[PDB]
Image (cartoon, rainbow, N blue to C red; front, side, top):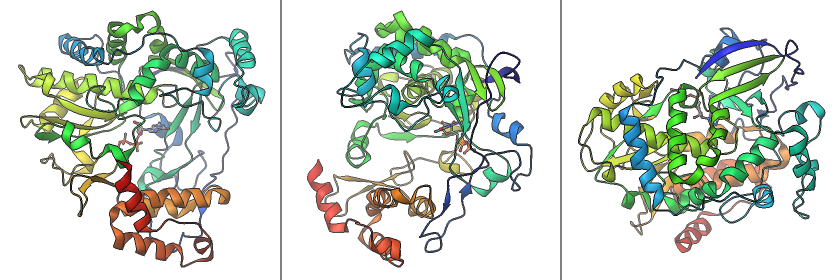
Length: 461
Ligand SMILES: Nc1nc2c(ncn2[C@@H]2O[C@H](COP(=O)(O)OP(=O)(O)OP(=O)(O)O)[C@@H](O)[C@H]2O)c(=O)[nH]1
């Protein structure tokens, strides 16, 4: 990805976008009961913690577009992946405005908490207005579409969340490139059924894990994988994507019946952005907050791994590449070992920066013992080994519980963490409950006991 030009939004007729300058994150009732070194991310240029320019930092993720055309390898990658997706009989039809708005099987209703985007964020109009669950009315939306059309600018916000001390000092704050409600609705009508097919089929056929339920999916993963596992992390995956990767994605879409709307992909690739008082244009880069960002990122990842394998190992049998991606995160396997380090070298030629899995210093062998997917490890249940526990490290849970945004969501926030925590074992879980109950707020929460979670889990398969 690369910014082509950035200039004052007033110069081109665009209103300044107001974005809070104060984090909504504050120490929680458990701030001193657990250990943690993370803090809220910088939201403005004036933050005293900054040790470098904020603007240069937030936009440095756009490292450039390393490649131009779609080469032979990418093309074969496209053919093979499109091939697998073909076996799903994905309904190529357009999704009706109603289902796209309020949901249907395989697709959840639009989230009312996320920004409505332009021009609404300038008008003031919000989502709770335009639509409402009960009536499942399209009228207002259906009207607003004709009123403002599509291909509307993306409102860029700094993501209010926790970041390491380094990310704070280097101004490495993540951005939320918000999609207009209109576009979000259009794209969901355009690809609605595709999204549903993926959500309903997480695995090695879609090579996607989007919409999955870790408590149940983790037991299926090991079986779907080939003998030898391999993985690696990406640095700035989204922002690093070059236009050619979007064209490759369009080729896949065309081959499975969505050629009549690949135009949408062009806006993800060549996009118009609004941030604060400035406006900018980006060539390449997957925007973080559009409808389908995850799924399209996962699809592109399926193309990238295939490509690197074809360019590094002529003769490789893709039919035996078993991989599952979630955006840039991925768990892959092959019957034979492969040099991740070498693959990373090839990745650099495609504009991708790949490094050892889980911040390792060097590329080492990936095992069922050290492999993670979505930050969770895989651990067979001590009593019934065929059931696999997705294990989120307690450190992550500790970092999170130490802060709050809304005291009203303390119950849900803590309950949610408990659903992640218990997989670490009964002992660890009770120590976690004990610390939570060591202060008034915790003692008042309705928290599930271990036995209850475990038995429920056992019965869920
Ligand atoms: N900008 C942005 N990225 C998001 C969001 N949600 C998930 N991501 C993903 O998070 C990535 C950014 O991660 P960072 O922590 O900044 O760093 P990194 O890319 O993992 O690279 P490292 O510095 O090596 O850890 C993007 O490339 C996306 O894949 C979001 O709301 N905004």
